[PDB]
Image (cartoon, rainbow, N blue to C red; front, top):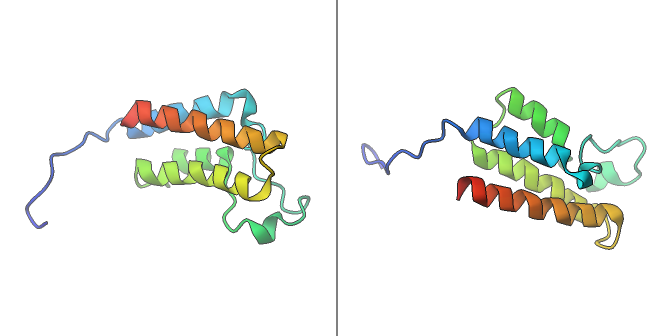
Length: 115
């Protein structure tokens, strides 16, 4: 509350560390469904169904340009990528499986880096 603060967590490395995690996600072999925005002209259903499209290139641009106020907003967009993927793709598809694998990969890096 006013003039009463919990001790200051060092967030000065968060930008660099989110960038490193993002690099590792970018270079994973199962990243290919997530590298670029889904083409909304060429994928019937995507525009109407997926209210907030997100992909790694868009996260990368937001990160590089100071559009994440803190590391939680960054993790929300990463998770959005996988939530969207589950909404649109069957679990037993190459893309569906890719999404599950990447989410697992991300969450481990997230815990090991920050928790």
